[PDB]
Image (tube, helix red, strand yellow):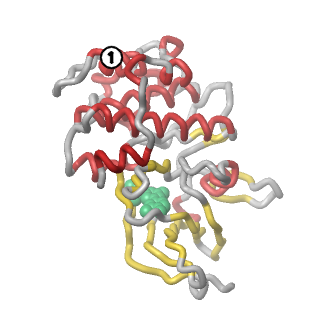
Amino acid sequence: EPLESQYQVGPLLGSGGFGSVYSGIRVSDNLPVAIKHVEKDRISDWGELPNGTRVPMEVVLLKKVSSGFSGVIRLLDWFERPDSFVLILERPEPVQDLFDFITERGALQEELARSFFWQVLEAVRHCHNCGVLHRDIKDENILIDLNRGELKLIDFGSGALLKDTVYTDFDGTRVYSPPEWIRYHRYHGRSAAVWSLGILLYDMVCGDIPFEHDEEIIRGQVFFRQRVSSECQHLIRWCLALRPSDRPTFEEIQNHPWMQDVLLPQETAEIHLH
Ligand SMILES: Cc1cc(C2=NC(=O)N=C(c3ccccc3)C2)ccc1O
């Protein structure tokens, strides 16, 4: 009931702008959890709980996306403390961050990249159905459940409620930010999400990001360092259309020729992860 009696705390999993995440175990059912600490001092994204109380946007957003669809990590609980917020999140076991998976394996085979991409497409589509906008889609914010071959979207610390009017604030990662942001500091949610999705696909199949500097983004020319299929190249260059309204919708991305005949997660695991 207190807090540190209900969860067997463990070793640091990582830390950065999101805060400090620790491996953990819920005492009782021995459920594997992740305990995320973030201090009020450095919280930039604040939100309002359904019942008034002021709270880290992440709590607001995870609450809006909690249920049976396991494409986004589940918030199991949360606590306020005098100077910080603590979040209890699910923890697949074994697990691996997409960034580390790609770092140690290089460019992914298209079949595997297809399976993964599809899964993050289903998970962003879910977030949007719940009025949630992630704003920081990238390899680091995606976990892999190595047993099931299921991806989980994580880290909603830069998200926002989904809206159809313009955004004038951006907290997410720069090299993942669309030409609209760089040039005008204005963007719309869906089309910006699609841009970052295009960066993600490229990263998956090439092993690295397509653009390093602002001028590279504004130019939007995509050079391919590795061998990549023609359909995949066309989907990538589409998501990375300079004009936002030129970018495909989620339905359009999922109906794209490259996106056909996706493996189910468990097949993915047996052929590519086991
Ligand atoms: C294993 C696990 C990790 C996380 C992370 N949450 C986060 O906000 N940020 C994370 C992160 C850590 C290091 C590098 C990049 C992201 C990880 C949430 C639930 C989990 O079960």
Residue that appears at 62% across and 65% down:
76
Q: Nearer the viewer, residue 186 or 62?
A: 62
Up/down of 50 relative to 219, above or below: below
Residue 172 x, y percent position in the rendering: 46, 42
Disc tally is 1
Crowding at mark 1 (Cα within 10 Å: few <14, some 14-19, many 20+): few
Residue that appears at 29% across and 31% down:
110
Residue that appears at 68% across and 59% down:
55
Task: Specify the amino acid type for callout 1.
Answer: Glu
Q: Is residue 227 left or right of residue 112?
A: left
> Ligand 1: which quarter?
bottom left
Q: Is residue 56 left or right of residue 212?
A: right
Q: Does residue 219 show up?
A: no
Q: Quadrant of residue 215?
A: top left
Up/down of 153 relative to 250, above or below: below
Residue that appears at 42% across and 21% down:
239
Residue 21 x, y percent position in the rendering: 45, 67
Q: Nearer the viewer, residue 43 or 112?
A: 112
Q: Which residue is mark 1?
A: 231
Q: Does residue 128 show up?
A: yes
Up/down of 21 relative to 118, above or below: below
Q: Is residue 18 left or right of residue 3?
A: left
Residue 103 x, y percent position in the rendering: 23, 48
